[PDB]
Image (spheres, coloured by chain):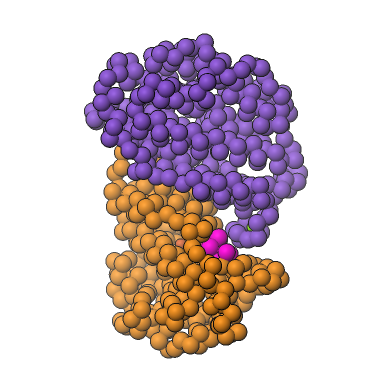
Chain colours: A orange, B purple
Amino acid sequence: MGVEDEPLLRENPRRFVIFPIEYHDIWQMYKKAEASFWTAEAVDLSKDIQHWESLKPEERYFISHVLAFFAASDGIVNENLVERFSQEVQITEARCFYGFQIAMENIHSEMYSLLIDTYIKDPKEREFLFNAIETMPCVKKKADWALRWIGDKEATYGERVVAFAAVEGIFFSGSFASIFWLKKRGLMPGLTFSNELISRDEGLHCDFACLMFKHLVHKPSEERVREIIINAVRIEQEFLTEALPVKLIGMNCTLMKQYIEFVADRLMLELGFSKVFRVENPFDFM
Amino acid sequence: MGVEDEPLLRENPRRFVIFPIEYHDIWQMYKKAEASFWTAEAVDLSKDIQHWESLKPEERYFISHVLAFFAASDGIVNENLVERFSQEVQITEARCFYGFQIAMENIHSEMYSLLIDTYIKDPKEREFLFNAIETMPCVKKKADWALRWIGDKEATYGERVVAFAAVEGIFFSGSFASIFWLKKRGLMPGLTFSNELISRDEGLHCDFACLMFKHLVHKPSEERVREIIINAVRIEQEFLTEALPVKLIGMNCTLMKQYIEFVADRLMLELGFSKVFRVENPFDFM
Ligand SMILES: [Fe+3]
Ligand SMILES: [Fe+3]
Ligand SMILES: [Mg+2]
Ligand SMILES: [Mg+2]
């Protein structure tokens, strides 16, 4: 109390001793992660270029900007895992998971940067896109919001796992949808297949956050969680309708605002709470 | 001065941005780590038990004790990477490597534990072996030595990479030789195969240490490195001849003493220094 009453956060003199397994649910999340390991090199990019050149200039803009956003955010997710989550959490099973997630975030980042390098030959444009945190106004709101939660010294782990479930779950959901939309139009198999791997990986990272949440003894209030989730939805929605609008690739903005609300509902439920928006999923392809 | 003079350790505002790669040498080692990924499940242990049962009782004692030593040490290595190296090193390329070494250490720990669970069914004997740091005097020296370098708030990164290259290079070399000895005797393909994978990985983790060392501007002196490596050789030698004698599996304690000295000379050469012992490699199987 406040931390020593938490099985997840209290001193474990066996934290670096692997066996035996005590938390089987947490352990299996780690085994699932491990069993789905992939490298960036596995993704065949060799047919993507022709599709990319056939695209309209504004689509190539949207897509390059989504890639840059993803690449930048992974780094923020990674910072939090490395500096906080993997430090403060004391159960071995959770540490293995987080250890592996860090590895995977690096492969996610590499993939996004391979996609960028493959499509965009201009090194000035590459640099612009890689430095997206400094160079892209559209990512600011999202990058700032996530970095806040790293630097926040008061906030409990419970509130902070929520925020990063919001990052990997809500902040990514519009862009994931976007690439799945492109699959619907038979465009860029390399991008869209890599997109399947990464969103699966990200959904798993949210599942894990939810599982960590359940094992918390002192959870934040439904009130407080709602506060964070709604806040994250609004930002995502502003990102997708204003800062980098989805019309750029032929999508309905209104329906996207709705889907972001559906994702948040699903995450709220997964966190042991009640829906907030009570809306259906408008996308049969998600 | 203090440490802002070090390319490896000075502020890197781009530390979580993957691209572009600037340290190609360091990055290719990450790619090599990543290309050699494996899981414990991949190793077939089915054919091992009949050989296990054929051994003399003091051969089983020796092996299970080498296994327990390994699972213990991995956790210390792990602690160090998690709490220290991956935190303090600022170049993106190196953080990827360490990020991945952490994941591979957890797989190594699992492997060793699986070996133990497979050969040893007695629950009490399992607990005794997993708790080897508290329960096994033979590993006290090696463990305390390593742990001292995590706690040491004054030693430089330059000294501590040497220390952990000694841990993964010298503290493991005798035990690795043991298992290759069993391979020569045609015993236990599962054990000896998993031993092939792990000694390869640890060679790499040592190679990586050497590469980091080479990139430091303020290296420790040859004298100071000698002192550390020599201290390590004596502890490993005591281990293999006094505390857990390799005699117990039919090896010569005099030739093993020598092999440790040869491993250390090789490490010293790799750190950019001169030999210490000048003895040749007595085992034709390393
Ligand atoms: Fe993620
Ligand atoms: Fe290692
Ligand atoms: Mg444990
Ligand atoms: Mg960088």
- Write down the region rendered in magenta: A110-114
Residue A65 found in image quarter? bottom right
Left or right: A248 as drawn, with respect to B41: right
Location of residue A113 in the rendering, given as x and y in whole percent from the top left corner: 58, 64
Residue at screen point 33% across, 58% down: A211
User: Does B270 appear above or below B232?
Assistant: below
Examine the structure image and report whether residue A112 is included in the region drawn in magenta: yes
Residue B6 found in image quarter? top right
Q: Foreground: B68 or B48?
A: B48
**What residue occupies the far left of the structure in this picture?**
B122
Location of residue B46 in the rendering, given as x and y in whole percent from the top left corner: 27, 35
Residue at screen point 67% across, 38% down: B213
Main SS category, magenta section:
helix
Residue at screen point 65% across, 17% down: B277
User: Does A149 appear above or below B258?
Assistant: below
Examine the structure image and report whether residue A240 is included in the region drawn in magenta: no
Q: Foreground: A247 or B279?
A: B279
Note whether residue B243 is visible. no
Location of residue A91 in the rendering, given as x and y in whole percent from the top left corner: 37, 46
Note whether residue A208 is visible. yes
